[PDB]
Amino acid sequence: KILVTGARGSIGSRVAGKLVERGLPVRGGVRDLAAPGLPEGVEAVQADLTRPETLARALEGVDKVFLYTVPEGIAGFVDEARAAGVRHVVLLSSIAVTWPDADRDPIGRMHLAVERPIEESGLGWTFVRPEALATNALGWAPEIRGGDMVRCAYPGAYTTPVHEEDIADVVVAALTTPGHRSAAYALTGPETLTQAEQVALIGEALGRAVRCERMPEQEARAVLEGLYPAEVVDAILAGQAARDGRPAEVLDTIRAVTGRPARTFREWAGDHVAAFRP
């Protein structure tokens, strides 16, 4: 049995589906059993890391777990995993842990505080460490739906966005094929792209020009305070200013693990085109 936590999510849903396709018994962690909103063949379970007694029942007879970095409860998970006889944990982490002075960064520190307890536990592990998720572009969907323009603080800020399906394929490979125990994979998409480049690629999927223009930082800060705590807004804008005009690193890891080219953001945009139009 494999437990896929967050089995309703972008990545977890695809992992669980692909595992059922291979004829494997899959448990899917969900918020509510009346739902469950999961692929055919996945057994819905509560796997709430803030209630470790739910974890104990979720892990009964489970061989392997796909885990997403919970903000709370990793020590409780490690305990119950050990006691249940789990042999392999695949963790969705972040490429931030690989950067210099990752302790000095909040995002880096958050992910390190989940990796380290797993690393020190005695459990078999694989870490999957993506850069920016392509799915972050869905945040522009409401704006793109109504306009020919996305306004942002840093149109020139680079990321290397990774398609969720590639992440899911790497996770599935780590769970079902040999050579991934104690491996930590840094995943990027095949191209480093500016925000403005990404917007234009969504325009291409839609078949119409979508521009990306600079807005003053204070305006951008105000709007972002509509979505986030003022502290987090400050950190977002600092990260974007640092990546402004700075191509991010492109890694070959997806191809090296899966044997298939990494999916492009152009491909991503086409796959998700329905989100961007009426």
Image: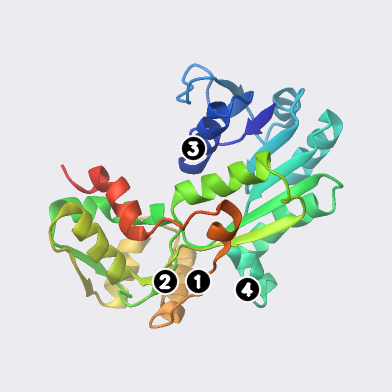
Distance (Cα) linking label 1 and label 4: 14 Å
Q: Picture quarter containing residue 171?
A: top right
CB within 8 Å, label 1 to label 2: yes
Q: Earlier in the sequence, mark 2 or mark 3?
A: 3
Q: Earlier in the sequence, mark 4 or mark 2?
A: 4
Distance (Cα) linking label 1 and label 3: 24 Å
The amino acid type, in three-letter code, at marker 3 is Arg
Q: Secondary structure at mark 3?
A: helix
Question: Observer-nearest residue: 226 or 18?
Answer: 18
The amino acid type, in three-letter code, at marker 4 is Trp
249 shown above or below 173:
below
Q: Picture quarter containing residue 266?
A: bottom left
Q: In the displayed image of the protein, which residue is found farthest to the top? A: 34
Residue beneath label 1, please? 250
Residue beneath label 4, please? 99
Q: Position of residue 193 (x, y in %)?
A: 37, 71
Distance (Cα) linking label 4 and label 3: 28 Å
In the image, what residue occupies the spot 75% across and 48% down? Answer: 125
**61 relative to 185 in the view: left or right:** right
CB within 8 Å, label 2 to label 3: no
Q: Residues within 10 Å of mark 1 (few under 14, many from 20)?
A: some
Residue beneath label 3, please? 14
In the image, what residue occupies the spot 76% across and 50% down? Answer: 181
Q: Picture quarter containing residue 275?
A: top left
From the image, state whether disc 1 or disc 4 is nearer to you.
Answer: 1
The amino acid type, in three-letter code, at marker 2 is Thr
Residue beneath label 2, please? 192
Distance (Cα) linking label 4 and label 2: 17 Å
Q: Position of residue 4 (x, y in %)?
A: 61, 34
**131 relative to 270 in the view: left or right:** right
Q: Position of residue 100 (x, y in %)?
A: 65, 77
